[PDB]
Image (cartoon, coloured by chain):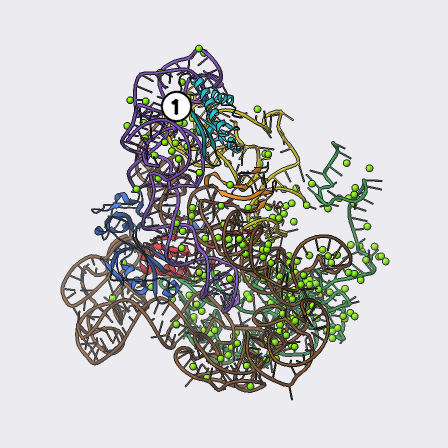
Chain colours: A red, B cyan, C blue, D orange, E purple, F green, G yellow, H brown
RNA sequence: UCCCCCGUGCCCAUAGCGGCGUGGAACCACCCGUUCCCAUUCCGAACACGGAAGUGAAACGCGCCAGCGCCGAUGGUACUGGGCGGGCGACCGCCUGGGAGAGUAGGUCGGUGCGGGGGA
RNA sequence: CGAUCAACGGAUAAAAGUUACCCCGGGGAUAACAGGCUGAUCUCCCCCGAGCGUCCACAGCGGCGGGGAGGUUUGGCACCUCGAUGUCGGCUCGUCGCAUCCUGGGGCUGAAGAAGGUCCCAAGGGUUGGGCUGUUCGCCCAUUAAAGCGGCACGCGAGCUG
RNA sequence: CGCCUCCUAAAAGGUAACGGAGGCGCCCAAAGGUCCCCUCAGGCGGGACGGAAAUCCGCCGGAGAGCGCAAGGGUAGAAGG
RNA sequence: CUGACUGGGGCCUGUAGAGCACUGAUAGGGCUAGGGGGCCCACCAGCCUACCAAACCCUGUCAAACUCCGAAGGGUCCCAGGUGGAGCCUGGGAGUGAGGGCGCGAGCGAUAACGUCCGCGUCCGAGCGCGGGAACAACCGAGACCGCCAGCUAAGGCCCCCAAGUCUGGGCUAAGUGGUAAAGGAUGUGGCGCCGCGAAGACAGCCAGGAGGUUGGCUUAGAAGCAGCCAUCCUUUAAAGAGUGCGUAAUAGCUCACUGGUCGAGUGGCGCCGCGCCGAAAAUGAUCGGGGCUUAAGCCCAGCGCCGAAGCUGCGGGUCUGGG
């Protein structure tokens, strides 16, 4: 599942989660999108869960666009150790996501299929979401 | 993309102007040789001398020497004595050398 | 078609006041003029969803003028997903670069075969005269299988309109569908851990 | 459990030491730097470690000459 | 004090790439030679000297063209010094002063100082 | 000129261990207990509805993921206590919580009946004797309506045991 | 455990943790002084043995090469040859 | 007179933000080396690819150790304001070198800790003196020289405990929400927008009908609209999907979308905002500080008045410093 093929640095500092999303705020590929309403580190496991739930709803058909990528290494100390003695080990990868980011888009599917696949996908994510349809506002960006 | 010609010219001239003397610049064409003493602080030429301006005659080396004497005679008259020689793209040799040796005979100090 | 929208002039009114009065701040320009305007947001929304950046909007200014415009730019509040400002570009007699809709006529054979028609471009950038704006540009996609594509070179353009993009720019593609039968392969798939780019004496 | 890092060198206190308009004396250091981030201009020398220093009493003046670089001059009083 | 050219600066691509066109009287270049000065890790290509039959082909200069490159508002927004509020938090707002970046309209096939030769 | 005086401002020219036989001065400036803050881990409860259940997502189940509660586990932290806050287990004596083991009242069932399963209400009372082991726990024997799980400084040593 | 480079470091300087990454304890008689000359990597095309890459030719190519060694800064109008 | 602080002016900077031109990352598509695999060959070529995919490009993004950009600020010098328990110089005497909470910016930790480690600020330390916050070092208010049975305010308050409004106007809530919590769930309530469908008679109710090809096609072990598929086509019609949901092992059957009659005016579906509901279990006796409160004594919006400290004022006094 998603993670960088290679990287310059093994561990990243934690950073902040302030502000509206930086880009990716308009539908770019398909007909409908799933928009983040609150900030989070979405894991790679969560992205894959949202993805599999969407192809499973479609069974055979449609196209899913995943517009977030987890390049941020997630670190955790081994259980029961004290503070100190260096940074914890990389245990996973997360995509930073801020309000307004279009995380997923779908195409090649009916409106009922897209509304439902995107809804189920939303239940796999640790944040509130919103389903949107491509507008002329999207097309003008 | 610069030529070996332009790099050579920039090279010898940056070193000259760093000393802050009035510079004796020399341009050598296939036919003629020209000299002007330039104040790089004001970007202004103080005095000139050309084989073209003097309508000078035959052997290029002997011509160059005489425009050197010519530049000196006009230079001293204005008060200019010390100077830095600017061979620009040319080797200190031949026509350029002759012009330098002719300027020195007139008492230009370099 | 051709749509109309009342606009108004503004000077020192703070944008946040205009937006709280339900008005949308905007600007109006070309090589000759530049004016600060505003439009009623509810009214502008009704037009813009019909006339995108594609169709002419004529602004009825309160001074009695009537200027033909294209919307050149719509700035969105990235959080709330709402328009916060509009550029109206006022057209002249000279030609103009602009986006003309694409109409994908036909059902691709690949789409009959199970595929999906990925509409990579939904409009196309074009130099054309304002007296000359086509409503759309038809493209036949019925011959595309999985996975063929069309480019702006394959575009049959009406009279007086010329491509303003590289004819190698791709405009449509028919790709394979999502398939549950793929899932189990992807679940049991193995991905060796990421490599860290070597630094120092080790390079 | 142990760290292979934990090393860093002392800070070197680099940067410009006299800004435009400041009255300096000959020998005053104007810029501490690694390489020629600034170049010596009129009445300014440069030492083996790229340090710019004033060659005369006077006033510091900076000049940004685009692709030719940024320069520090000392205008005599 | 105007136009062309030749030197030499300054601004530091609005000055660049590319395409086309143009100039040899003058100037510049290529050019003609390699005796002489000087020269090639081989080569008169370069550097250099002595020349003056030819050509503006190359180069250089000067024009035109916006395909690229470069520059680029206005408006709006992000962010923010200072002042205030809100949320359990992740974080979110308001006031006052400041205010990008991206993008849009557009701009650009340079401007200018000093000396020299020529022209009117 | 002679320094891995590298513990690199370099105590001597010259130096390792052990103490449950231990001692003094100090510290809650700092650990082991208990409490506290926290809740990763732990226990419990939910959201989503892939898929199972012949048929049928939801009788009983719940892939991949998502949200919480509690403060009984193991820890994190080091905040009162080191001019002392006695420790496991048992016995004795209780008392409380309810996420209920039984008894009482219910809905659903893939509930014929009888017997079950699952969830809801419910803390009034009740919740056995023995073999093993210091044990808590657990396994086993014989029963039982049932042989509940937790808190009270892992309740209770100025109450006993040891 | 001293020293160097980058980050953390909140656009002067400085700034901690058993925070995130690397290096030093040398070397060079030229790899130093000065004078003179020269300009890269890379792409494409062409060339016996000859290859992805040996050496040659042409075109494009402002610096992505090089600068003994880490990293950074600097740098061809040279600090590179 | 040089100070903190401030005004103007110049220079220095690479953070916030943003960007992708460099260094890396990155999804998809295009294009296209090289591989895989498939035809065809060993005579050395050739073609096919819904396979992995370099370079390049397009769309769309990510970065403390990336930057084509780049603030607000900050630093420093000059001129000016600034006479302050300001500043500078020399010397005598120290104490301190366990900090801590909070706000903001980061690292570590788990986007844990009354956690830990730096930065800017602040308070406590030393203001455990005073008002407010039920109580409470550091939250809000405010820097206590002494005295007064005088006055004004601050935060916070004005139904009673308890000093001052059971003050005024508009709205919301019915949950004692207020008076601790999340995903998520819901014909709770109110205010908005947006579709439709309807007096060319809607919705609801009642009333009929809802049909031949079709026990249909992948199909056999059942698959007959309604166990999965690579299908939705006709026919008679007012109308009718080879079918919404229920049922059969199959079938049938009910009944939906569906059309006609019946009444006679609304009806169904979205989306957004305010306030509430559930989700909500822990251990001695409960409780918002208590009582008690419902067109509030709750919440939102707008006001007038008052109460309220050791702050400020009036009066009197002390001491030190400065000026007479
Ligand atoms: C006793 C003293 O004199 C002083 O010390 C203080 O008290 C205590 C100190 C330590 C202590 C427990 C220790 C060291 C321990 O290791 N305990 C574990 C475990 O936790 C325990 O539960 C048992 O488990 C099975 O065996 C034990 C096991 O060794 C218990 C105390 O009460 C102070 O208040 C007293 O005055
Ligand atoms: N004027 C300013 N500096 N504003 C700073 C804005 C920061 C504040 N948290 C806000 O979002 O409003
Ligand atoms: Mg951190
Ligand atoms: Mg996480
Ligand atoms: Mg972590
Ligand atoms: Mg441990
Ligand atoms: Mg650590
Ligand atoms: Mg960690
Ligand atoms: Mg993880
Ligand atoms: Mg985001
Ligand atoms: Mg969710
Ligand atoms: Mg964009
Ligand atoms: Mg709208
Ligand atoms: Mg180590
Ligand atoms: Mg470190
Ligand atoms: Mg060290
Ligand atoms: Mg230091
Ligand atoms: Mg340091
Ligand atoms: Mg440093
Ligand atoms: Mg500096
Ligand atoms: Mg030196
Ligand atoms: Mg040196
Ligand atoms: Mg200046
Ligand atoms: Mg100067
Ligand atoms: Mg010229
Ligand atoms: Mg000038
Ligand atoms: Mg050109
Ligand atoms: Mg011509
Ligand atoms: Mg030309
Ligand atoms: Mg000629
Ligand atoms: Mg001629
Ligand atoms: Mg010879
Ligand atoms: Mg001879
Ligand atoms: Mg020759
Ligand atoms: Mg020559
Ligand atoms: Mg000749
Ligand atoms: Mg020519
Ligand atoms: Mg030339
Ligand atoms: Mg033009
Ligand atoms: Mg600029
Ligand atoms: Mg711009
Ligand atoms: Mg602006
Ligand atoms: Mg602020
Ligand atoms: Mg804000
Ligand atoms: Mg502001
Ligand atoms: Mg402002
Ligand atoms: Mg900015
Ligand atoms: Mg801009
Ligand atoms: Mg140009
Ligand atoms: Mg010029
Ligand atoms: Mg001149
Ligand atoms: Mg002139
Ligand atoms: Mg002239
Ligand atoms: Mg010794
Ligand atoms: Mg070492
Ligand atoms: Mg030591
Ligand atoms: Mg020692
Ligand atoms: Mg040392
Ligand atoms: Mg000693
Ligand atoms: Mg010694
Ligand atoms: Mg000795
Ligand atoms: Mg020893
Ligand atoms: Mg020793
Ligand atoms: Mg001993
Ligand atoms: Mg012993
Ligand atoms: Mg022993
Ligand atoms: Mg013994
Ligand atoms: Mg003994
Ligand atoms: Mg003894
Ligand atoms: Mg013994
Ligand atoms: Mg003893
Ligand atoms: Mg003792
Ligand atoms: Mg002692
Ligand atoms: Mg003692
Ligand atoms: Mg303690
Ligand atoms: Mg200590
Ligand atoms: Mg302890
Ligand atoms: Mg202890
Ligand atoms: Mg302990
Ligand atoms: Mg412990
Ligand atoms: Mg323990
Ligand atoms: Mg205890
Ligand atoms: Mg403890
Ligand atoms: Mg205690
Ligand atoms: Mg306790
Ligand atoms: Mg706690
Ligand atoms: Mg918890
Ligand atoms: Mg908790
Ligand atoms: Mg947990
Ligand atoms: Mg729950
Ligand atoms: Mg469910
Ligand atoms: Mg099944
Ligand atoms: Mg069922
Ligand atoms: Mg199923
Ligand atoms: Mg369930
Ligand atoms: Mg599970
Ligand atoms: Mg969780
Ligand atoms: Mg959990
Ligand atoms: Mg506890
Ligand atoms: Mg405990
Ligand atoms: Mg612990
Ligand atoms: Mg504990
Ligand atoms: Mg610990
Ligand atoms: Mg402790
Ligand atoms: Mg302690
Ligand atoms: Mg501490
Ligand atoms: Mg103790
Ligand atoms: Mg005592
Ligand atoms: Mg005591
Ligand atoms: Mg005692
Ligand atoms: Mg134990
Ligand atoms: Mg008990
Ligand atoms: Mg219960
Ligand atoms: Mg019962
Ligand atoms: Mg019962
Ligand atoms: Mg029964
Ligand atoms: Mg039965
Ligand atoms: Mg039975
Ligand atoms: Mg039952
Ligand atoms: Mg139930
Ligand atoms: Mg129930
Ligand atoms: Mg009971
Ligand atoms: Mg009881
Ligand atoms: Mg009981
Ligand atoms: Mg026995
Ligand atoms: Mg026995
Ligand atoms: Mg026993
Ligand atoms: Mg036992
Ligand atoms: Mg026994
Ligand atoms: Mg056991
Ligand atoms: Mg066993
Ligand atoms: Mg029995
Ligand atoms: Mg029973
Ligand atoms: Mg028993
Ligand atoms: Mg207990
Ligand atoms: Mg315990
Ligand atoms: Mg224990
Ligand atoms: Mg105990
Ligand atoms: Mg116990
Ligand atoms: Mg006890
Ligand atoms: Mg005892
Ligand atoms: Mg005991
Ligand atoms: Mg006791
Ligand atoms: Mg006792
Ligand atoms: Mg006792
Ligand atoms: Mg006692
Ligand atoms: Mg005993
Ligand atoms: Mg014993
Ligand atoms: Mg040191
Ligand atoms: Mg720093
Ligand atoms: Mg820094
Ligand atoms: Mg700094
Ligand atoms: Mg300093
Ligand atoms: Mg360490
Ligand atoms: Mg090392
Ligand atoms: Mg040598
Ligand atoms: Mg090459
Ligand atoms: Mg080749
Ligand atoms: Mg070959
Ligand atoms: Mg080759
Ligand atoms: Mg380099
Ligand atoms: Mg190395
Ligand atoms: Mg003053
Ligand atoms: Mg000052
Ligand atoms: Mg000052
Ligand atoms: Mg100031
Ligand atoms: Mg940033
Ligand atoms: Mg990039
Ligand atoms: Mg871009
Ligand atoms: Mg970032
Ligand atoms: Mg970024
Ligand atoms: Mg950084
Ligand atoms: Mg940055
Ligand atoms: Mg810019
Ligand atoms: Mg500034
Ligand atoms: Mg700073
Ligand atoms: Mg400043
Ligand atoms: Mg300052
Ligand atoms: Mg300033
Ligand atoms: Mg002053
Ligand atoms: Mg003082
Ligand atoms: Mg003082
Ligand atoms: Mg004084
Ligand atoms: Mg003193
Ligand atoms: Mg004294
Ligand atoms: Mg004394
Ligand atoms: Mg001390
Ligand atoms: Mg001391
Ligand atoms: Mg100390
Ligand atoms: Mg200390
Ligand atoms: Mg301490
Ligand atoms: Mg501290
Ligand atoms: Mg500390
Ligand atoms: Mg803090
Ligand atoms: Mg702090
Ligand atoms: Mg705040
Ligand atoms: Mg914060
Ligand atoms: Mg902070
Ligand atoms: Mg940090
Ligand atoms: Mg959590
Ligand atoms: Mg602390
Ligand atoms: Mg904290
Ligand atoms: Mg913290
Ligand atoms: Mg502090
Ligand atoms: Mg103290
Ligand atoms: Mg205070
Ligand atoms: Mg204080
Ligand atoms: Mg206090
Ligand atoms: Mg206190
Ligand atoms: Mg008090
Ligand atoms: Mg207080
Ligand atoms: Mg109080
Ligand atoms: Mg009170
Ligand atoms: Mg308090
Ligand atoms: Mg406290
Ligand atoms: Mg006072
Ligand atoms: Mg009053
Ligand atoms: Mg008040
Ligand atoms: Mg009250
Ligand atoms: Mg009262
Ligand atoms: Mg009031
Ligand atoms: Mg009232
Ligand atoms: Mg309730
Ligand atoms: Mg209540
Ligand atoms: Mg309550
Ligand atoms: Mg909720
Ligand atoms: Mg909710
Ligand atoms: Mg509702
Ligand atoms: Mg509502
Ligand atoms: Mg069928
Ligand atoms: Mg039927
Ligand atoms: Mg509730
Ligand atoms: Mg009212
Ligand atoms: Mg008062
Ligand atoms: Mg008073
Ligand atoms: Mg007072
Ligand atoms: Mg008085
Ligand atoms: Mg005094």
Report the quarter where the N terminus of chain C lies: bottom left
The picture places residue E39, in percent across and down from the top left corner, at: 48, 18
Crowdedness of circle 1 by 10 Å Cα count: few (<14), some, many (20+)? few
Q: Mark 1 — on which chain does it sit?
A: B
How many badges with numbers are in the image? 1
Mark 1: secondary structure: loop
Q: Looking at the image, can residue C106 be seen?
A: no
Q: Quadrant of residue F13?
A: top right
Return the x and y of residue F117 as percentages of the image width and height.
48, 69
Q: Which residue is mark 1?
A: B52
Instruction: Identify which residue, C118 or G40, lies in the foreground.
Output: G40
- On the question of residue B91 being in view, the answer is yes
Q: Residue at x 53, y 28 (%)?
A: B82
Foreground residue, H288 or E112?
E112
**Vertical position of residue D50 compared to residue A59: above or below:** above
Q: Nearer the viewer, residue B107 or H295?
A: B107
Within 8 Å of ligand 53, the CB of disc 1? no
Q: Dividing the picture into quarters, in which one does residue E24 lie?
A: top left
Horizontally, is C165 left or right of G39 in the view?
Answer: left
Which of the pair F129/H129 is nearer the observer?
H129
The image shows residue A2, relative to residue E87, as above or below, that is above
Query: Where's ligand 110: which quadrant?
Result: bottom right
Q: Position of residue C7 (x, y in %)?
A: 29, 62
Q: Name the residue: 53% across, 44% down.
A: D61
Left or right: H89 in relation to C148? right
Residue C170 position, x and y percent, is: 31, 45
Q: Is residue H157 left or right of residue C175?
A: right
């Amino acid at each position: 599942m998603l993670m960088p093929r290679r990287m310059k640095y093994r561990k990243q500092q934690r950073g902040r989660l302030k502000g509206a999303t930086k880009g990716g705020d308009y539908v770019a590929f398909g007909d409908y999108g799933l928009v983040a309403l609150e900030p989070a580190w979405i894991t790679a496991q969560q992205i894959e869960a949202a993805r599999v739930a969407m192809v499973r709803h479609f069974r055979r058909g449609g196209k899913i666009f995943i517009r977030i990528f987890p390049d941020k290494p997630y670190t955790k100390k081994p259980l029961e150790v004290r503070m100190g003695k260096g940074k914890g080990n990389v245990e996973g990868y997360v995509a930073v996501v801020k309000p307004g980011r279009v995380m997923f888009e779908v195409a090649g599917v009916t409106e009922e299929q897209a509304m439902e696949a995107l809804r189920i996908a939303g239940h796999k994510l640790p944040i509130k979401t919103k389903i949107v349809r491509r507008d002329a506002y999207d097309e003008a960006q | 993309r610069l030529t070996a010609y332009e790099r050579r010219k920039f090279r010898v001239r940056n070193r000259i102007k760093r000393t802050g003397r009035l510079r004796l610049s020399v341009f050598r064409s296939l036919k003629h040789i020209y000299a002007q003493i330039i104040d790089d602080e004001k970007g202004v030429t103080l005095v000139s001398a050309s084989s073209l301006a003097l309508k000078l005659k035959g052997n290029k080396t002997e011509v160059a020497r005489q425009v050197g004497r010519a530049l000196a005679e006009k230079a001293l008259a204005l008060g200019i004595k010390q100077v830095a020689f600017d061979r620009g793209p040319y080797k200190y040799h031949g026509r350029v050398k002759a012009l330098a040796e002719g300027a020195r005979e007139g008492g230009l100090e370099f | 078609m051709e749509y109309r929208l009342k606009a108004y002039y503004r000077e020192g009114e703070k944008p946040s006041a205009l937006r709280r009065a339900g008005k949308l701040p905007g600007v109006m320009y070309n090589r000759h003029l530049n004016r600060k305007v505003y439009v009623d947001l509810v009214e502008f929304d009704k037009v813009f969803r019909q006339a995108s950046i594609h169709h002419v909007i004529v602004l009825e200014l309160p001074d009695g003028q009537s200027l033909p415009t294209l919307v050149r730019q719509v700035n969105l509040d990235k959080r709330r997903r709402r328009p916060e400002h509009v550029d109206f570009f006022v057209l002249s007699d000279e030609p103009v670069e602009m986006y003309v809709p694409l109409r994908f006529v036909g059902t691709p054979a690949g789409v009959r075969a199970g595929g999906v028609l990925q509409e990579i471009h939904r409009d196309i950038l074009v130099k054309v005269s304002p007296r000359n704006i086509p409503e759309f540009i038809e493209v036949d996609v019925s011959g595309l299988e999985i996975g063929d594509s069309l480019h702006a070179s394959d575009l049959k353009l009406p009279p007086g309109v010329e491509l303003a993009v590289s004819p190698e720019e791709t405009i449509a593609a028919v790709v394979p569908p999502e398939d549950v039968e793929k899932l189990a392969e992807e679940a049991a798939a193995e991905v060796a851990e990421p490599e860290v780019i070597k630094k120092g004496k080790e390079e | 459990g142990s760290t292979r890092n934990g090393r860093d060198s002392q800070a070197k206190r680099l940067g410009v030491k006299r800004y435009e308009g400041q009255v300096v004396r000959a020998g005053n250091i104007l810029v501490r730097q690694r390489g020629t981030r600034f170049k010596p201009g009129k009445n300014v020398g440069m030492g083996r470690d790229f340090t710019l220093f004033a060659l005369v009493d006077g006033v510091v003046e900076f000049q940004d000459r685009g692709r030719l670089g940024r320069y520090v001059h000392v205008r005599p009083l």
